[PDB]
Image 1 (cartoon, rainbow, N blue to C red):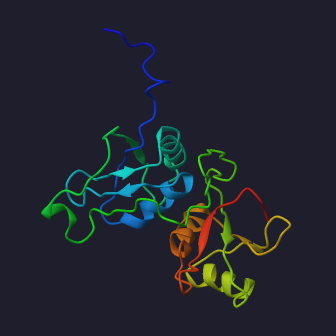
Image 2 (image 1 turned 180 degrees about the vertical axis):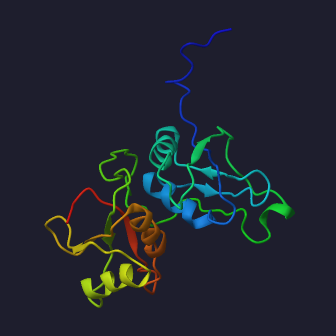
Length: 208
């Protein structure tokens, strides 16, 4: 019956899926990271050895969408991705089978953000697959040497290395690839600096 216009009103749903997993190469935190940059990931599930899927419960529709829009042939690890949808309400903690190790996890309101909009959706930052990673939070201890020594000890192509808009606390770097600048993120986001001043990292619009 009544379709050829389903949506607007009731549209957006927050709960995603992640499919076309290679087994090995996809992890629970690789996944958190990108959903949690594109949006603000709410809670994170895996189908371990069940489907070659991930259930990734996102911030809302236009969030979820962007992560599916950006991920969709971002070849993270290096399989043609097919992250799609679920609608599925929320996730509340399941199964023996299921939880035991951290197939499940409960990420709720992770405090890293970078958004921290009080009930905004502003969207300036996000930037589709580029090699140039935005770095933040530096106490008066480390420097560009040590931040750059970090994207240099992970394996890295570290193209360039900089300081942000005007102000200058924040830091910017560029690897050679996303394949890398992505991998290097998954490394450095919330990089356990010490006493909860852990590293914040994403994909920048500025340059080198």
